[PDB]
Image 1 (cartoon, chains in turn purple, orange):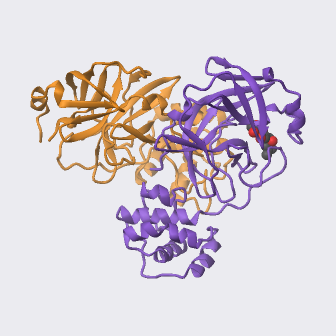
Image 2 (image 1 turned 30 degrees about the horizontal axis):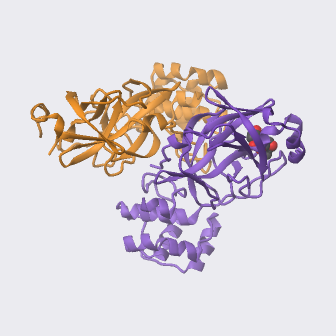
Image 3 (image 1 turned 90 degrees about the vertical axis):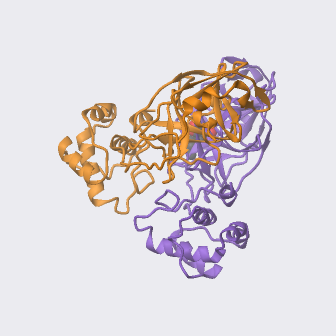
Length: 295
Length: 291
Ligand SMILES: *c1cc(O)c2c(c1O)C(=O)C=C([C@@H](O)CC=C(C)C)C2=O
């Protein structure tokens, strides 16, 4: 099963931020609340907002921040790229050990979907190669965050900003820089063609071998270039020498050379799965990383 | 469409490690009682005997760093109830409930008292759970959360050879015809949860996917013969009633959606996908969709 991280450490950091008539989610760490800058926009500003102009007109008491039943007091504010940073009275007593990190396409993380400051659900994700997320967003999940948890330390890698016309989601890192070419404005912007994360499918095939399925193996090998020429006809991401290097341990553990697993995938794409399953799926799964598989 | 698990924070604060001799597994600490699988006292065992021979100093409970002192022990069916010196200050509001096949819940998978991940499950019609349990996940619990109140419905006991998992409710009653002993046991043949497929087709309609919709209607009887041929649970009037809110919401009557389903089964997706799948999901309940 694809699993998400236990969400407790993140749940204790979720707050509700309201400015005027707009409300979304915020993240309370130490004495700062982070949230999307869009909170300061009104209906009429969405098309062409001037965030510098809208923020200069605000004072500290324009921002209503609620942690459960407690109103937090804002004592300063500033903007860093597309995230608003609200200084409050009180350091979050439940602040975990944490860091901000920027991730790359193919990486996985968990998302705590929240509504008006209250967590609702948790799910496991990958950053797609077109810099989008195939999320499940309730209407007011703006400001919900994505994370990884390693040894009790939480890495915040994503903050939700908006839904694209195709149903997918776009957002920023916790420094307010968007993933992909998207902007916090209601324009016509659309996601690029999405491709399958090849290195993740191969890692998962190695996971199938480790758990004993070998049905899809064959006796062929391939060159890297030949593999990529085939795979790209199926909208699979090109495989690099870095990806090959990354799969080396798994190859070592299983005794199957990386380009041999590549030949198996070429054939799986040619034939389908003929009513069969691999780990437990009937689809080529691309949201488990090489790092994930070792775990 | 993503399946979502419930936020697990309220359960995370209840997870402890329990050790008896050489055996270590997970426990649930609520108030001054730790709940865990009785097979923690195993070396065809007689659990009546083995536990009379036990005393409090035989159990080592660890809540993270702190060792808890067992001051009493008792058995309820297949779960051991270890009374400890201190109440868990992180005890949520909670209830013990028993679910039925087809209902969904979240599992907090744990390793030696330490939460590792969370995922959303359904109780299969053969009473097993298609889960991913790591080494030492015994004693992990399943739950729903409703209004800040945790409903504990499942405790993990065993991996079946087929890879699926078997467990009890929190009162130690097994789900399915399984026993906590090393007999040879296998899951019975499983079936697809029809009322959940229908709910997921409703969700697909609510999401703008309408290609599978057709002009026809079927009967409950005609459908169940198709269902039976495809290893689908039979559909009942109760199921139909359950789906009424969705039928009302979408203007698609249940037996008209059934017709759509009959056709999907007989003829296939045919290059089309429904919600981003080419197989029909059966681990979303009608309730899950309404929410
Ligand atoms: C949060 C909530 C929202 O409703 C929106 C945004 C955030 O961050 C946002 O950034 C942008 C929009 C709006 O432009 C709709 C988006 C498109 C038309 C692409 C939000 O609505």
